Image (cartoon, rainbow, N blue to C red; front, side, top):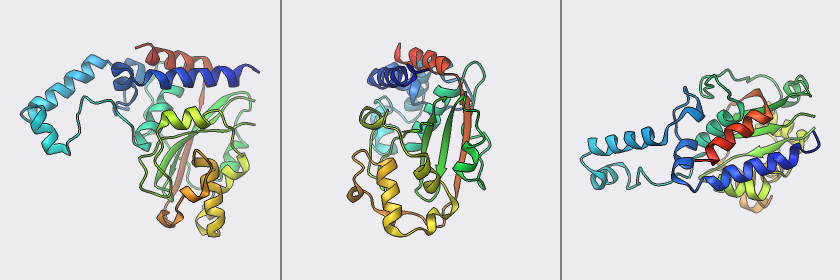
Length: 246
């Protein structure tokens, strides 16, 4: 009810904070999507890393052959990795959900779809925006309000932004369902450059700074795909609480 926004804010806040812990981080950003997220075992995951490193003839050679990264290091997830895993955390109860395997809509408008969603359920939408080259989540708490959840290593039209920072700065900053419709519509790709820029910084840049966005890097013939999924707010809290509790 009326307490939803505040609790939601608190859940995300504690979840994010926990992500500086080794086990919380390992469990949160693992890339195995066909098993339950809360079923992930940090020790099991760490053994796999140790095994992989043993395969490459020791840690120093592993790094030398994989780009220099430390496989044991905490992770800063790419946008696909953060969208998929937070989608799982929000939607799962006792049956694994694989965001890479679920069905996506691709010839309907966001407006269209949302206007068909039970206003008394919560939904979260995973967006695969091939125009931006970006996956992110639209959270739609029960009632209308939408919120964005994302990370980005940068390189495209949008600046790099850590999920923690996006969440801490704009986690509970609601966005226009109308601007969302415009963004997530077939005809966005054929919109006037300044409008494209307008929507992008608005919805997806922490300071809403248009000067930090570069639409040249848009892929104008890219495909748009999204999938919504109902969720139970308490279950999401439970899931978040488990991870944060590691």
